[PDB]
Length: 96
Image 1 (spheres, helix red, strand yellow):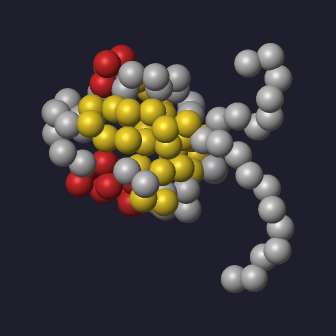
Image 2: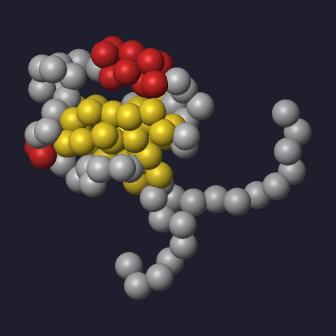
């Protein structure tokens, strides 16, 4: 790669816990990466707001990852333990 542009943001890490069934929320393949389909356990995903956009799981890069690749990483995750996800938010500053 070469590139030669700049452009930067500050993305939200949130923390989640892997109950038994593979968290208490579901995912969907979107044109933009994986998204939250639906939350099924609020404290299974404290701070998740649905339709948010998966970018990193435990600092692994998963934007360009297929649905399966993201599911697999969430399978690698330990049950009952924390997992740290990073989602897409904050285009620019305004009244927030």
